[PDB]
Structure formats: C-alpha cells, structure tokens
Image (cartoon, coloured by chain):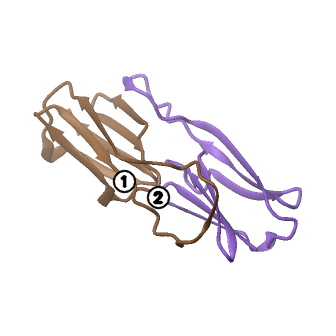
Chain colours: A brown, B purple
Amino acid sequence: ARMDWKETPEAHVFKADLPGVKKEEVKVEVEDGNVLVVSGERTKEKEDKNDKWHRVERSSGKFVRRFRLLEDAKVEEVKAGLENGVLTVTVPK
Amino acid sequence: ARMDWKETPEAHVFKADLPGVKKEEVKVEVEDGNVLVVSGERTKEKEDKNDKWHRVERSSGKFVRRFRLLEDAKVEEVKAGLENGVLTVTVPK
C-alpha cells in the first residue's frame, strides 16, 4: 500500500495504490480522534483452479497503516473513494 | 508495472497492476509479430505550490513490459481489459 499524503489548504488528501482491491477488502478508520488508519488484504483471485502460473510478481497481502493528523478530524466529513486501483481519503480541515 | 503470466487451456493470460492509469494512457501491442508490449504512463499530479507534501511513496512516469508470445498465437485475437487498476491481456492459443 504505497501511499501519498498531501496537504492542500482545504484538506489532507491521502492516496493509496491498491490495484485489484475491492472495497469489502479495504478499511478506513479513525482512532483516538486524530489517527487515520488504512488496512486490508486483497482477496485470492477466484480464477480457474488448475491454471499454470508461468510468472507471478503481483503478490499482495495483509497490511495496516496509520497517520497522525495535525488536528482532530470530523469523522462525518471524511470522504473515501476507491477507483482505478487507487484509494483516496480526503480529510477536511 | 507488476505483471503475472498464467496459462489456461484456452490462452495465456497476463495481468498488470496499473493503479491510477486511465485506458487512454495505456497501450497494448504486438511487435515483431510475436512480442506483447504493454506500455503507458502514470502521470504525476504536479499541482500547485499552495500544496504541501508530507509523504510520497507512489511512483509515476513511464512503464514498459514485454513478453514473447508463441510463434503460433492468435495475435489477431488478443483482448485487453482494464478494471480496478488491473490490466488483463488474453492471448488465445
């Protein structure tokens, strides 16, 4: 989960490369008022059991990440969207 | 760009993690008659100086991937799909 953290004047924007991940496999939470938490685990591709694996580089697993926000976030204002393999978490300041 | 290479009884299937890449930035071709070429660019969101970066782990720029297909592969029947940051190329046998 390679991630970026940008602070525009309007909000804190986090990006996470989570290719091939479904929302039911990712989790965005807030702890102790100012700690953004991103975790998950890409599911096994329920693809043809018996296939021959010539080469496998894409090998993702479980993970958890945390960031200390500069200010307590208004959890009901935090937006999180998943698109084209990129998770985006916007935190309004 | 991380890629998997699996083989089904019907075709060789290639997967590529391309988070944050729109189908207009990816190119799928067959060079020299039997070389699969997956390339494109993961555009950097330069933005404005008003912004402030606290963390940067995600990569950007050009990517190039080449696999040598069989001298007898349905080169005219290769399909390419892009969904949830994952590219899939199906080369019929």
Could you tell me residue B13's position as x and y percent? 65, 65
The residue located at (10%, 33%) in the rendering is A32
- For mark 2, what is the residue? B84
Q: Position of residue A80 (x, y in %)?
A: 28, 49
Same chain for labels 1 and 2? Say yes or no: no
Within the image, what quadrant is residue A22 found in? bottom left
Q: Mark 1 — on which chain does it sit?
A: A
For residue B47, above or below residue B70 = above
Residue at image point 58% right, 58% down: B87
Q: Mark 1 and 2 residues: CB-CB less than 8 Å, in contact?
A: yes
Dividing the picture into quadrants, the one containing residue B69 is: bottom right
- Whether residue A73 is visible, yes or no, is yes
Residue A82 badge: 1
Q: Type of residue at label 2? A: Asn
Q: Dot 2, how many residues are within 10 Å of its Cα: few (below 14), some (14-19), or many (20+)?
A: many
Tell which residue pokes out farthest to the bottom in this image: B10
Tell me the element at label 1.
Answer: strand
Secondary structure type for disc 2: loop
Q: From the viewer's perspective, is B47 left or right of B14?
A: left
Q: What residue is at 67 percent from the left and 76 percent from the top?
A: B9
Left or right of B62 in this view: A59: left
